[PDB]
Amino acid sequence: SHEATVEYLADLVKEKKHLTLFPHMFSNVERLLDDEIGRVRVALFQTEF
Amino acid sequence: SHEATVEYLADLVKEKKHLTLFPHMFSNVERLLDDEIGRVRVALFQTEFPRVEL
Image (cartoon, rainbow over the protein chains, first blue to last red):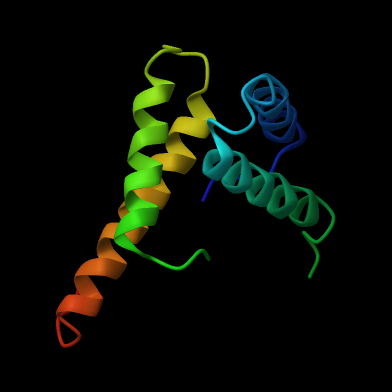
C-alpha cells in the first residue's frame, strides 16, 4: 500500500472534497477513500510502533 | 473489508465507469478502486475454488 506521508494525506482529502459534489454516485469509492485517509492518519503517528 | 458479492463488484465497476468522465482528476481514487475490484474478483474466485492458490 502507498507510503504514509502528509502530502499523500493532503491529496486524498482533496480528492474526497471533489467527490463530495456527487456523493451518491460514488458511494463505494468514498468509503474506500475514507478508509485510506483513516489508515494514513493513523500510520503518520505510529511509525515507532 | 466489505463482503465480496457479485452485486458489490457490479457497483464498483459502475463507479469506475463514472470516473472515466474525469480523466486524470482522481488518480488515488482510481488506484484504490482498482485495488478493491481486484480483491473482490479474487475473493469471488476463491469462494468458487476454495482449494486454489492465488
